[PDB]
Image (cartoon, rainbow over the protein chains, first blue to last red):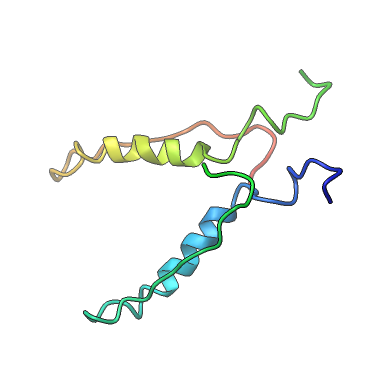
Length: 49
Length: 49
């Protein structure tokens, strides 16, 4: 896996609108006060930006 | 220009959040009714999706 540059298999263009769609589904349950639904993701090992 | 595959010079990852930032700047002026500010872009010649 380390012998290639992975520009076509990781972080494609429309990837962030799928993750933003998961956040909207979890917003239908986080409206009542005191029951906010947390959403966290794991970080990219290679980049911090 | 047609002898290359343009994957590093067109439609990069963070491009749509810049265009969505232009839309927020134009929202400070489109609040009063009857003075909505229109925003249109030119289409990609090659793709429709």
